[PDB]
Length: 224
Image 1 (cartoon, rainbow, N blue to C red):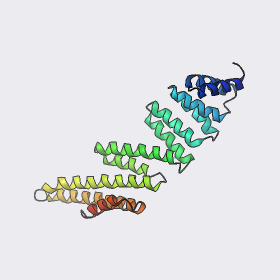
Image 2: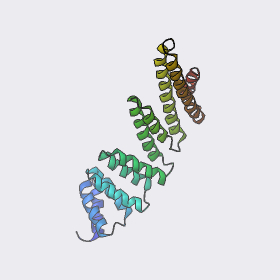
Image 3: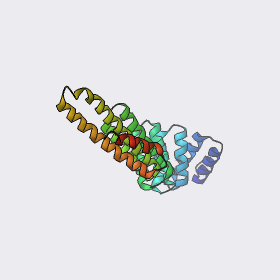
Image 4: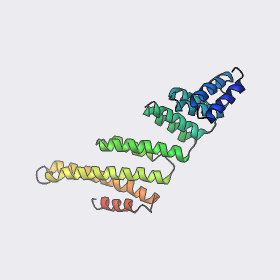
């Protein structure tokens, strides 16, 4: 077929039958011949491309929808998913970051953004990298959702509570053998516990129904 309207109708027929490869073939040709102006078809073409594993092509079509301000939350999610499928985490989170800036307070984009950073923080916390765990959990607090902010703050509270306890653990044998180092370690533990009390306090304020957060803040206060 040569007629662009015929190509779009053929692509619609293919999509209706779940033949994503034909729909991609017909829509991509239609968009090429009509100067990429139909954002509804561009969005559908991006989904079809991702379904047949043409990930770079998918990202290109979702970009058309984004530039035409069409179905923005879905177009950013689609573009991010294409980069996730290409196993490109940096472009995955960069796209979600652009999406949260364009459509603030979109439930699905905020969930993906926050899950990414909570998982990164967890990964660094498990590998004992406190500074990088903190950086990642702090990014998960950038969401507008009070619920998602609460669990990023609760994760920061636990991170610093565990760090202060670990420092206190290593300082016990020093109390009667190296008082110089004992004072240094005690001050480090105190600083960690004070950060923990403050992050947990912030979480309790946003989610007073989360009684376990209040209980953990009480445990940290008992260490100061």
